[PDB]
Image: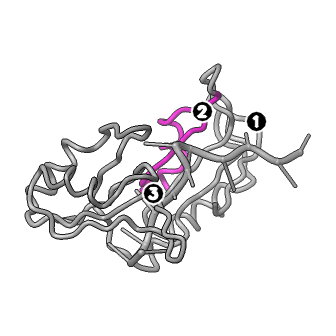
Amino acid sequence: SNTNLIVNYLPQDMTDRELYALFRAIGPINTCRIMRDYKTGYSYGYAFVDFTSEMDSQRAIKVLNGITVRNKRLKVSYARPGGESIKDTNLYVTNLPRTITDDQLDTIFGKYGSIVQKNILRDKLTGRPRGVAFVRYNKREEAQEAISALNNVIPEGGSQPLSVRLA
RNA sequence: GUUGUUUUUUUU
């Protein structure tokens, strides 16, 4: 947790030119990479921004986090050290009680490790949960643990066995 | 009974 940031939810048509102007506005930028699939060069939808000062980095988070750019809302946060340990940490859960909430998810899945991002898919019309959700842990061991502890078991408040697998 | 994130969080 220092100067390196990971920018998420970037519109596909965002150029390095844009990333720069946007983040440069906070303080001097060391580097700005958009991360796109080699060959086709299509944005993986995220980027890293290495500021020069730990202070500038922090402030970027405070100001740019959540700002809307065209169709998306950016999500700026400190990058976690890479590695094999961050691998296979995204979970695809289904058969979740339809009365589920972000706080229950936290209770159920938060004991096995530290959640980095979670999303309860909701019906666009009703706004009610569809029973699906994506939970992304910090370490690869937490997801594995989460999986074996919750797969095929009935969650509290529900009458149906959860389904937890790697996305 | 096949629900899939603001499709895409580790350097593409």
User: Where, by quadrant of the figure, is residue A31 drawn?
Assistant: bottom left
Query: In the rendered image of this protein, does residue A43 appear above or below residue A156?
Result: below
Residue drawn at x 19%, y 43% is A62
Q: Is residue A139 visible?
A: yes
Q: Is residue A122 covered in magenta? A: yes
SS class, disc 1:
loop
Q: On the image, which quarter does residue A114 sit in?
A: bottom left
Sequence-first tag of 1 and 3: 3
Residue A52 in the image: state x and y as whole percent: 10, 67
Q: What chain letter is assigned to the residue under label 2?
A: A
Q: Which of the two marks, 1 or 3, is nearer to us in this view? A: 3
Task: Tell me where the magenta segment starts and ends, as one range.
Answer: A100-123
Q: CA distance from mark 2 to mark 1?
A: 12 Å
Q: Amino acid at mark 3?
A: Gly
* Above or below, A154 relative to A18: above
Gap between marks 2 and 3, in whole Å? 28 Å
- Considering the numbered disc 3 on the image, is that residue within a helix, a strand or a loop? loop
Mark nearest the camera among 2 and 1 is 2
Residue A28 magenta-highlighted:
no
Badge 2 element: loop
Circles 2 and 3 in contact, beta carbons < 8 Å: no
Quadrant in the picture for the N terminus of chain A:
bottom left
The answer as to whether the residues below labels 2 and 1 share one chain is yes
Which residue position holds label 3? A45
* A153 with respect to A138 (left or right): right
Residue A100 has which mark?
Answer: 2
At label 1, which amino acid type do we have? Ser
> Residue A96's mark?
none
As drawn, the residue found furthest toward the top would be A126
Residue that appears at 68% across and 37% down: A131
Give the residue at mark 1: A159
Residues tagged by mark 2 and mark 3 found on one chain of the structure:
yes
